Image 1 (tube, chains in turn purple, orange):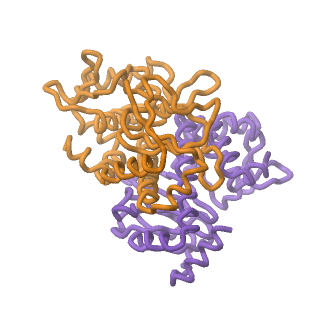
Image 2 (tube, rainbow over the protein chains, first blue to last red; image 1 turned 45 degrees about the horizontal axis):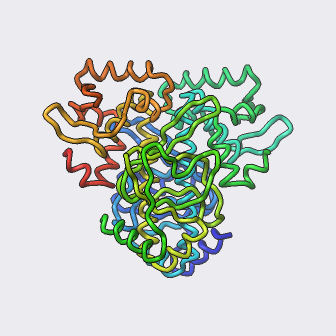
Image 3 (cartoon, rainbow over the protein chains, first blue to last red; image 1 turned 90 degrees about the vertical axis):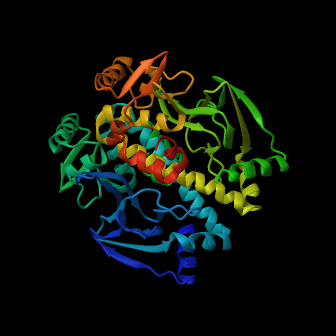
Amino acid sequence: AQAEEFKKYLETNGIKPKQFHKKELIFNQWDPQEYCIFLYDGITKLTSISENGTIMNLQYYKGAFVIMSGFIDTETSVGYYNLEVISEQATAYVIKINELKELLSKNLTHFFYVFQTLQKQVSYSLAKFNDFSINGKLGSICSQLLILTYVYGKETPDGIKITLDNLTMQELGYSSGIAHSSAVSRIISKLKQEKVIVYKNSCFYVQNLDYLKRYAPKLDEWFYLACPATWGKLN
Amino acid sequence: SNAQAEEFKKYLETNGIKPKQFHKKELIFNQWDPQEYCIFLYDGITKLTSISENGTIMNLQYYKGAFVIMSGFIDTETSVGYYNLEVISEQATAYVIKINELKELLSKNLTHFFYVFQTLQKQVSYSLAKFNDFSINGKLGSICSQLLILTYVYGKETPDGIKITLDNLTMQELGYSSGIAHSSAVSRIISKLKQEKVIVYKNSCFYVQNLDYLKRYAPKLDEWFYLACPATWGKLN
């Protein structure tokens, strides 16, 4: 993997792996230092918290990927957010945004690795913006379940199980723009009656992937074009 | 800087890639016959669109001035997705780099590799800010957010308020930016902003009277403009 070789390149340049447990914040929106984090193992989400305390979930990040809170060119903030750990365990190499440019200059197979993750991210946020915007809040819930089925799902004799040890009703609402937790509950019950989803084991299971797929066409296309292994597993 | 953009332009010309002229309503690329490029848009105004099977038009984003727009992945040479890039100004000039030539060019001069990397970091951050603000307060917040955006980039101080100087900009086009397909849904929001004295529609142009009001609904974007485009932000203070 490129991830494996980047991991090694990091350890060889004195950058060591740091472990985290559930609910720990790799960075926070008040930290005045900026970073590049190479998330290597684990599951994570990016949040923003309002002036009043309202919480928006911007995105899940899994597996090996990179997340940046600063600009290389200027070293200043891209904007203020948190990266929270969701899984029982995660590991990440934290680099100061001031050290990045020199690291990537030196070994440009790694420069292209990070640019690749930037292209994926660029393209992903666009697809997601298209699908969340059309069909309003119905399509938002269908779009987020589709993302979670492709990334975290698993084949199972009773459907496709979403392997998120938590995933609460309120948590889904934070990812859509939904303030009331009962509004989410309507959407979830409405999808249950039509045999789209089921809920057992403290876990969500999907059963008409085709239905979701119809509310989230730009994203399905994106899994196909950007992550064809992940996509082919359930297609 | 933006001396960086001029420098990239010069580097491309030296290396045999020539400028190209496009005209209002032309497509540089389209979603039905996808081609893979780096578009270096040098001068003029464009919009990235998608049209769904039922005829629903989504305006994803406006692109101006100097900027970079990718339609393929360099590592794999395939599509990032199916979109249209449509010219809004009367003229626009762009450098159309084939995706299979880009790596070579960026590999021989890291200065320009980093200018492209920076532009893409600005895109990522812009999309997150816009997603935050469009999501939190329904369609009211989406329309206020797109107005603040167009006010910073295309606005001009006049005696009647900040005039959005953008060729068309109709009710319907404004609705396309936030997944609104019926004009009646937009006018309902614009009616409220008019009653509340935030905007005036006059001489076929929107004039903004209370930018501070739009900031309440678009707090992540105003922060993004502050951090990412301080000259543009400073102009309107």
